[PDB]
Image (cartoon, rainbow over all chains, first blue to last red; front, side, top):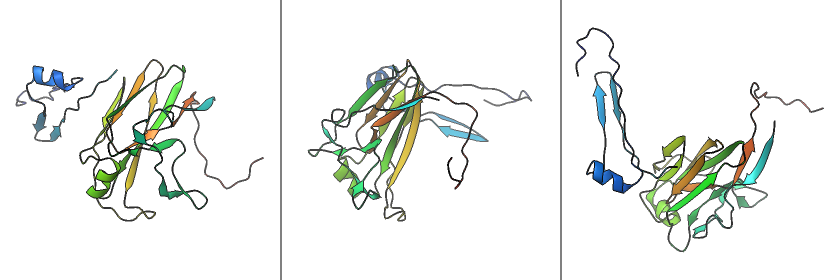
Length: 54
Length: 164
């Protein structure tokens, strides 16, 4: 996405974490996952950590 | 205002398939090696370190302060003889807290006759919230937790002054 609007754009996103390895292969078909959200002045690589939580 | 010390993970029963007799020569006590009375050093027993999982519930109706550690051996040799697994991790997760400690192994300068590193961590567990510890090595287990009531608005004064 390019910010041609001449103003600051607020883009929000999420990163999902299934509770076990079973939910990861049926929603996304890949154990090892990642998300690359990078811009000209921002960078982050979200390594999805899977664990059973309360 | 109010503050008590209680054993959150009993030393004798929380770890049947583990070793809790680990002691550090750095944590001496009158010419004898030792370790933190409130923590525990869990190493492999019988040549295997099973995947552990402990869920403490805060029924005490007050904020509980559970502290734990993450160990870092200086080389790949110490990792296979204490925990029997190169790739390690620790899953300390609760209802409103989550973190995955990837153990990074490296040779470090000798601080207090040690090339190893035990990075400590502490979280507060609210009532009605259950914390879960999950690990397959390098976990410095919490033995003594505390239930406290908050005194807002204070600090800490460094002083050599006597008490009266």
